[PDB]
Amino acid sequence: ARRLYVGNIPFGITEEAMMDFFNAQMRLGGLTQAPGNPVLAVQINQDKNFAFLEFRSVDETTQAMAFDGIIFQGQSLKIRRPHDYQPLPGMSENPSVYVPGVVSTVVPDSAHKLFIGGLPNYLNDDQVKELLTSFGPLKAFNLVKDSATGLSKGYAFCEYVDINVTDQAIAGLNGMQLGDKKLLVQRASVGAKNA
């Protein structure tokens, strides 16, 4: 739908670097119908050498297909439309397992809100939103500011729509370092891991 199938990718490169490469090309070529990042979710499977780039639209997505064969890190990124694939659901079980997080939320009540801490206060709202939105669709975004000063407190609460990208964003973002602060990303609730 809004995901492109890119193959012939360089084994070794990060999803972050490849995503920025595409974002840059979208901007420089004039493929962007809006500022920021056209890519909503970057999901790269380097094991089987295929990636699905989910864009914020379909227009830009279709426009990005023009770069089929683009030179990246020595490789030639093949850009085609993905195959007809349906995620096999469960009847009273899981076909196998997939990932603990899907089909687990049967009720609207769901502890899915992420707490993002370890951020500097010079980061403006737009940047923070853009960053987090580039790893999946956000349903809720509230940045904690100081009521008197006006600046950010350096942390926010944000909940993603999809249940897959949320933990994947944690795996990537949580562990980074913004200046002298280490980026801490987890869910606001957390029952009891003790790990």
Image: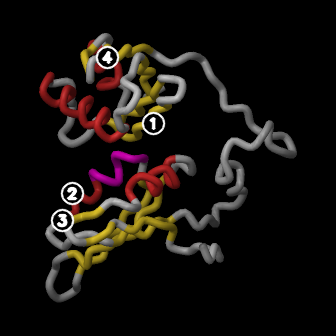
Chain-order first, disc 4 or disc 1 = 1
The mark closer to the camera, 4 or 1, is 4
Q: Which amino acid, by three-letter code, is at mark 4?
A: Gln
How far apart in space, not on screen, are marks 2 and 3 (Cα)?
Answer: 8 Å
Q: Which amino acid, by three-letter code, is at mark 1?
A: Gln
The mark closer to the camera, 4 or 2, is 4
Q: Which amino acid, by three-letter code, is at mark 2?
A: Asp
The answer to which quarter of the image holds residue 5 is top left
> x, y percentage for residue 118?
31, 71
How far apart in space, not on screen, are marks 4 and 2 (Cα)?
Answer: 33 Å
- The residue that label 4 is drawn on is 75
Q: How many marks?
A: 4
Asked whether the residues under the numbered discs 4 and 2 touch, taking CB atoms below 8 Å apart as contact, a structural biologist would say no
Q: Secondary structure at mark 4?
A: strand
Vertically, is 133 above or below 66?
Answer: below
- The residue that label 1 is drawn on is 43
Q: Which mark is residue 123?
A: 3
Q: Which amino acid, by three-letter code, is at mark 3?
A: Leu
The mark closer to the camera, 1 or 2, is 1
> x, y percentage for residue 92?
87, 45
How far apart in space, not on screen, are marks 4 and 1 (Cα)?
Answer: 18 Å
Q: Where does the magenta region start and end?
A: 130-136
How far apart in space, not on screen, are marks 4 and 3 (Cα)?
Answer: 35 Å
- The residue that label 2 is drawn on is 126
Q: Secondary structure at mark 3?
A: loop
Q: Secondary structure at mark 2?
A: helix
